[PDB]
Image 1 (cartoon, helix red, strand yellow):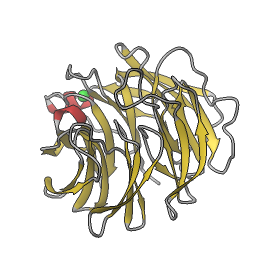
Image 2 (tube, helix red, strand yellow; image 1 turned 180 degrees about the vertical axis):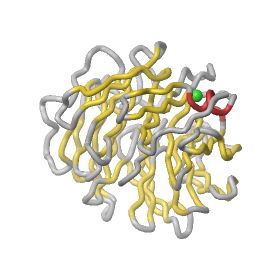
Image 3 (cartoon, helix red, strand yellow; image 1 turned 60 degrees about the vertical axis):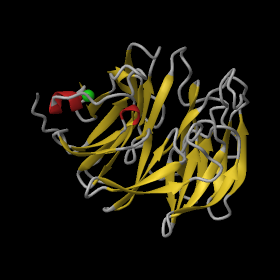
Length: 331
Ligand SMILES: [Cl-]
């Protein structure tokens, strides 16, 4: 059990590990030293993280790690990585969205409810019931704020964006699109971007050419659609800090101005017969980090790029690195 006291500026990489093998880990990268530290939760705390670390959000000096398949969210101190508390009772958590110090939503797979939680007391306070959704095929996923509203994508065996009114904690609208929207971002024009994964071969629910969509938040309608190829399996819409440049995964890493009418012919980073899996854009300097799962078995690798596409650094992380979380000194 180990004493960490790290940089005020930093990058966390969550490593899902192998679903049903409890080898998920946390990585911490220092961009100023170009040094990675691996398995930092375990080293810091004396216990393992669990199964499928999904995502992670930092608020007010505290890091909130969603461990999807261990029914828990760890709160760690972000400088020491020691746990300050945890929340148990999630069916299968995905993403955490704070509305205040005392109120956050936590999405779930295999549940039709979004859990309301109190972060100060470390408790579950309620549930938002999703319409046309059961437990066996249920999915809520990533979330964005638009005023009093929260928008959420319904991922596994679903095909909807839902609108929640946060003042009443209830689902007030929905929009049906292509199957299995994977992720959700809000650009600086208050237009949402989601990209579907197209389902999978043999799926009971379906399997189709996936799409990238731009959806106006005010009118909750599709303004643009970029449709890809059967067998494509896109994911991970991400924005730059000014929220005017969008990246995602589709074999390659792709980059497009939010105002563009076409995807550029050339990608940001070319497919190299691996598995680009995670993605993030540094919100201050526009540097792009690409998490490569490679073969879903070996140690993953993160590549760091300049906004102009030139490789800066690369570093080994844990198994299937899927998500990132910025610890920034200045915003
Ligand atoms: Cl760890």
